[PDB]
Image (cartoon, coloured by chain):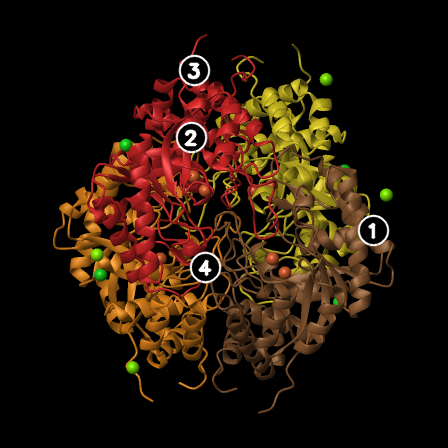
Chain colours: A yellow, B brown, C red, D orange
Amino acid sequence: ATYNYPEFGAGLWHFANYIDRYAVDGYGPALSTIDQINAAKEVGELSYVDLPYPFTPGVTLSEVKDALKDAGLKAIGITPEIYLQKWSRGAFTNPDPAARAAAFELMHESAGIVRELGANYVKVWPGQDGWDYPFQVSHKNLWKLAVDGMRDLAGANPDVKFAIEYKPREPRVKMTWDSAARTLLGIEDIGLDNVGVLLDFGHALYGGESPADSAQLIIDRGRLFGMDVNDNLRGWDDDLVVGTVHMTEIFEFFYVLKINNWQGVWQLDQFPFRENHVEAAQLSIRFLKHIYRALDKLDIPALQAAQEAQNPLQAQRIVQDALLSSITVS
Amino acid sequence: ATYNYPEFGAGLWHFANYIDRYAVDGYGPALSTIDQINAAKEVGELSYVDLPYPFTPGVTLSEVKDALKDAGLKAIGITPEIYLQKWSRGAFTNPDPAARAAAFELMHESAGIVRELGANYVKVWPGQDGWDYPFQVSHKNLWKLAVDGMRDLAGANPDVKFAIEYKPREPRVKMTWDSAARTLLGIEDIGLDNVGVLLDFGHALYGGESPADSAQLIIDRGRLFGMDVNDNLRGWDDDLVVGTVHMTEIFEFFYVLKINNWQGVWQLDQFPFRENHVEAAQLSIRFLKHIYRALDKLDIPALQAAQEAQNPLQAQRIVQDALLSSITVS
Amino acid sequence: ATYNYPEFGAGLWHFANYIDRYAVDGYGPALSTIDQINAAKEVGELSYVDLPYPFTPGVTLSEVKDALKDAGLKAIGITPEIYLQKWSRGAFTNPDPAARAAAFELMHESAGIVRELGANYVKVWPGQDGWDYPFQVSHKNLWKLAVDGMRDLAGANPDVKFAIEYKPREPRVKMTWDSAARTLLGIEDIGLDNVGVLLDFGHALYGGESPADSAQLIIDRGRLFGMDVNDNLRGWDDDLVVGTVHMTEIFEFFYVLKINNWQGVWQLDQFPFRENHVEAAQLSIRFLKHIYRALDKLDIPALQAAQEAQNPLQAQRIVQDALLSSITVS
Amino acid sequence: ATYNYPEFGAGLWHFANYIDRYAVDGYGPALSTIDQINAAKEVGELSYVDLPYPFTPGVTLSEVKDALKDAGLKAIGITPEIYLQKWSRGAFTNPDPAARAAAFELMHESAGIVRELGANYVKVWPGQDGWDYPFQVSHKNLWKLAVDGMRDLAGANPDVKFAIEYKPREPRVKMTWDSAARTLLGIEDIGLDNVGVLLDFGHALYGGESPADSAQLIIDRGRLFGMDVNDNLRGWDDDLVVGTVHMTEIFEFFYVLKINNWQGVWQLDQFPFRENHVEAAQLSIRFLKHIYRALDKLDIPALQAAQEAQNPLQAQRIVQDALLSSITVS
Ligand SMILES: [Cl-]
Ligand SMILES: [Cl-]
Ligand SMILES: [Cl-]
Ligand SMILES: [Cl-]
Ligand SMILES: [Fe+3]
Ligand SMILES: [Fe+3]
Ligand SMILES: [Fe+3]
Ligand SMILES: [Fe+3]
Ligand SMILES: [Fe+3]
Ligand SMILES: [Fe+3]
Ligand SMILES: [Fe+3]
Ligand SMILES: [Fe+3]
Ligand SMILES: [Mg+2]
Ligand SMILES: [Mg+2]
Ligand SMILES: [Mg+2]
Ligand SMILES: [Mg+2]
């Protein structure tokens, strides 16, 4: 058996070392944008990365281009870092209009970086936008800032795609763009063709969604601009290696992409805090290749017949037969 | 101080005795629709009930009209019982087309009952519609049945309002109409003016929503047809007496209704399994009256100024000053 | 390859038809204890059942013995129905002392049934014991009733084992015996050798525990009297077919049982509400047989070496190699 | 009315600025230990702080003593920082024995600081101890390291109390000392009189416990060495200002402390990321003073009568009458 595997990608931050409110001295040394690209190269199966912007201090666009070329990598997305201290109280939704304007300027500049690097989208994740307490915000006004600010950004760059990465929460207690459905509602309201969704399987999962259903819902609106995969224990954005907890639902997610003829980079968004980051990516790709092989074995017509009958026993037996196929025989 | 309190209502089932998968012999004796109306009368401050339909065996529409009249109650909604054994595998989404048709006939008949009783809406809660396992359903086809079937029902009855009561889950592992945002998306797809939302505070809460924000979002689309209140511990539809766990967030919910000038019956949807059902309703009304008085005391301009600043400490101080006002000074 | 598979069992209720607060007319017709035993026979690989007591109306102990014999089944446990209407406000913890006494009498009688049927244990699940609201109970006095009442029961029957099935909640908002750790604390307080634990994988899972760790903790105290398995989405006791959502963690559970040489019936506690109940049990057994074969393939020494290093990437690689082995190569 | 209010305290980190994996440049400038003590002074009602150890770079014990004296503050606890990069893979449970030894040395030194400052306890919070993936650890061996390491520490310092702050998780996916009950089990196993519990109301709440019950359970074992309060939305350690979400359950927690004659510092453990930290503490103390006044008004005999009857309606009516007393009338 021979397979034409999907192209794989990762957020560049898969190869950064992290920091949290406890290990304030970091989970390893600070790595530059260039160090992170060199790390992604070591994985040996990636074709794309999503690069945060601005790059680390001192790193230029020319240096990034060179590192990417030497790594055999292309930029799939550019993620403006609209969640740093400057925007700790919001980017689109900062109470300070000057802060909102500065956020726009960074995101607008990031669309230029997308043009320069031939990336697919500006990946918009406004992590500091939302609320921490009941009564902290006017719900009407907060959501208006979110939607209007997004429209302003996208409207100023009609030639570039903006992929909104919804997330239930973190760092806020509740984020503005919190679910697939609310994101699609917001997209309707914005009214622009160049705004779509970055569907993070893990975000959907711990948000209580069926990630497979969310993929279908978004695809049905023509708004699935990209995906991210990882795993978690359904309570938080744990950002674990894909396939280590929820094999079945991850398989369902890829099944829905398959039947909808949705082609895209299979993209990792994972944070291997305490692990070898390169090896974490490698294990992830091994599992994803298994998923690809399992999709080939899956008896789709039999599954769909079971689904028409809504017989979960038949559906699960068919799915297990494909998924519980040998990973060690590739 | 003197107050013109809101009109209060309850689901008629607030006065039924329940049954679950363990206490299969029930939490008390079976009470007829008429017995339930007579119990609702005992509360002493209800003006409306939402009546399940069909009525209990042998009970006629004429008997119901007489009992409601004598009890000082009007029907605010009629809830077709589309979640009984016949539709245990779905109403709109049953795999058997004949079952789907039969559900339509009942719901269509319930629209007639709404006309006869002058009720505001058919209250649509398709509790058996959804899935229990990953891979059990075609998500595309399941949602299409849900939306198309709702359109068929509402389109056949343009003079009657249909309020969709979204709910995360139960009795299914996941219900079709599972959130405010998805419901609004579905309403846009249906494309009819007579379809709206029954927002149950408790469903929003355990669904991970800000109930206040959901109210605002729905009101912004002109689709808030009614409300249900209760409390829970945010993990399940516990259907506890309102104000016993989450006083702050229920106050926020009513605050949003107030600032939008949303006028409508303050409706209880509670299941006092092991309590005196009449006294549970009475305690709920006492709390709602406190909420109403607290809303009158609330410094709304100062709150809104704090919200513009997104200062949660100022917002909470103002809220606490109103909410912690004496309940024994009525 | 040839395997000596574990003996399989199920709660007899795996073959009952259910009822809930919505489908009050049931998910199917009422089946007698004898009908349930006859259905269990159909599965074709069960050796044991756990029987609720009292049996359904009119069914005698002699009839049960004959049906079990003819079905090829033995009683592994007897479950006194201490959660029916009589005890809807508690069994051990009922506020009415006469109700507490009546619960004792039933449980004491069930110990006799265990003697008569040669079962391993009285399976104690005090589902109605706990609380629904903050402030409803004296936590000190509630827990004292729970512990002292359990001591009274077990102390009166020193020759019989009592397996306490802990569970987070349902039908109460919180149950007394709510976790592995609390149960072990209670067992230490009771101070009797014949009180242990029925560890339900699904209860542990939606309770936020690592079921594997709970198994180890209980085994370390010599208190693992039996197991129940099923699956869920980690928010509720969904009681789905085992292996349909959390294959990795159920494999870990059985792995812990294996390395501790815990020998005991692999017991299903599942509620196939809307499915063919016999085929649900069959699919469950097929999966458990896969688990057994996967445990034989698992490189336990390499896993344990990875665990000493706390390297999750190595651990998961090893686990996946075993678990993803072919299910259709039996 | 005149009140002798409880002594108030806060973790010193209530006055630090924070950092997370997104705002890696921090939520404000780095404040030294001394700056934080000066901040605590500004609150104007604190008597105690819990100080992390080591102090910030360059800060000496002599300087801390001087700052504390000038602030009118005493050290209630010392928190060894066993969750920094060095111990990012565990303190007691690090796979590297050298790391475990270094953790012991820091904690042992911190017991000396407790002696010097006359603090009540070494506050032990081993945040990096636990696991991130299923199968990552030997559950038996991991828990053995946790218990044995704690015994080694406490046994080496029999004159000093060690308060274990249990927490469900964060930064790990699951922490070793994860619940009140498991902590009490561990304490039994350690077998030393100087090991007890720091009960964080928020940790109990998002762990699914009744914080009030947990307080009772721990007090019944004589192990409640201290408390921490804050609030959250039950899904995560949000560390919000106390009383902003769950007034009722916080009241219940203090009620249980009251009836058990448990006297201690009312201690805040909150992280006002985006707020004025001093004002956050001030609002907290205002709410806690309200709680104290409400406890004075509470009709405890009537409540306890309701609790004996397990009547939650009566219990809640009595509680509301006390809690919903005017906060603005002190
Ligand atoms: Cl698409
Ligand atoms: Cl409206
Ligand atoms: Cl054992
Ligand atoms: Cl104590
Ligand atoms: Fe992502
Ligand atoms: Fe993520
Ligand atoms: Fe409702
Ligand atoms: Fe409900
Ligand atoms: Fe069970
Ligand atoms: Fe169960
Ligand atoms: Fe704390
Ligand atoms: Fe905390
Ligand atoms: Mg094919
Ligand atoms: Mg049609
Ligand atoms: Mg006694
Ligand atoms: Mg007094």
The N terminus of chain B sits in image quarter: bottom right
Report, in whole angstroms, how far the alpha carbon at label 3 lies from the one at label 1: 54 Å
On whether ligand 14 comes within 8 Å of the CB at mark 1, the answer is: yes
Residue flagged by tag 2: what amino acid is it?
Gln
Percent position (x, y) of residue A19?
A: 45, 45
From the image, tell me which residue sits under label 3: C297
**Disc on res. D29:** 4
- In the rendered image, is residue B225 in sight? yes
**Disc on res. B28:** none
- Cβ atoms under marks 1 and 4 closer than 8 Å: no
**Disc on res. C267:** 2
Q: Residue at x 77, y 29 (%)?
A: A261
Residue flagged by tag 1: what amino acid is it?
Arg
On whether ligand 3 comes within 8 Å of the CB at mark 3, the answer is: no
Viewer-side label of 3, 1: 1
Report, in whole angstroms, how far the alpha carbon at label 1 lies from the one at label 4: 57 Å
Total residue callouts: 4
Viewer-side label of 1, 4: 1
In this picture, residue B59 sits left or right of residue C209: right
Regarding mark 1 in the picture, which secondary structure is present there?
helix
Viewer-side label of 2, 3: 2
**Quadrant in the picture for residue D42:** bottom left
Q: Residue at x 47, y 84 (%)?
A: B328
Residue flagged by tag 3: what amino acid is it?
Lys
From the image, tell me which residue sits under label 1: B151
